[PDB]
Image 1 (cartoon, rainbow, N blue to C red):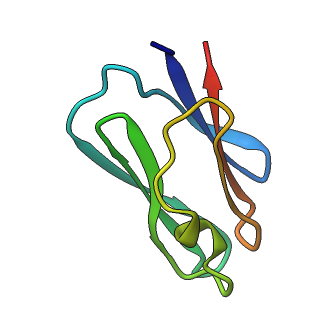
Image 2: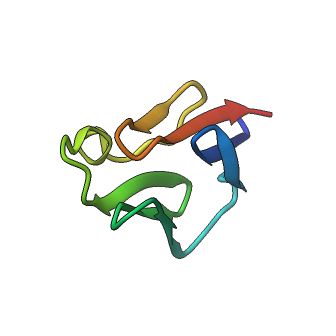
Length: 87
């Protein structure tokens, strides 16, 4: 099948590029913003989501798990973006 990488950015600056294909186990990391802003990122197997955050709108959290080429997650107030790209 497809081989994909998740690109996770904050204010356009890349924090992690994470190849998802073949990934097993669970990893969590927090992107800390200005003030008390945070996003708890979670990679579980070949999927990624914002597990939890204190954004006012919760749009990115509500988007849930992503895993396919072309998928995105956005948390606009915290300037966090996830893009999944085919390699």
